[PDB]
Amino acid sequence: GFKQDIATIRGDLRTYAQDIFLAFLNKYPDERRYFKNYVGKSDQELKSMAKFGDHTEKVFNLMMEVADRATDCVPLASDANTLVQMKQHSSLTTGNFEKLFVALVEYMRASGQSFDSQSWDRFGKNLVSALSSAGMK
Ligand code: HEM
Ligand SMILES: [Xe]
Ligand SMILES: [Xe]
Image: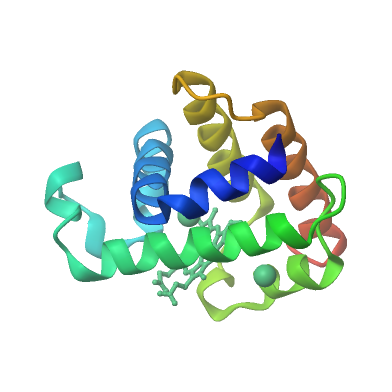
């Protein structure tokens, strides 16, 4: 279930964080624009830029932490609050997160792995509802 999936992702954080982020950029290519330094580079070319692996791992670490403090896939208001008020996210709308989670759920379903994708679906939706209640456009 969702709790096992957190263990799974944590177990190989770097690999899942890169594979899922690239699935996101690839499914929704106009999102690359928020990441100036990843414009014009292949999947393999990005995996040797130091900040790409740093960034992806830190994003999914934090995502995993938020996932963990959630109850029944409902995130803490204060976690939602940190995602709105972070400098890096000032330009973002909830539409951006919707996309990440649609790419994340699509990744899970495509893997041969028994992820609880429905639960990740719910979590993404609940995180988007909480981002808005917390003030994100
Ligand atoms: C739950 C999902 C997300 C989490 C947990 C998250 C978290 C983070 C974290 C932790 C960083 C800083 C990494 C570091 O210190 O090196 C970051 C930066 C950033 N985020 Fe997110 N984010 C999420 C979703 C998104 C989405 C959906 C977008 C746009 C589509 C986005 C855009 C950015 C950009 C452009 C940066 C700047 C890169 C950097 O500072 O390294 N984030 N985010
Ligand atoms: Xe992201
Ligand atoms: Xe957070």
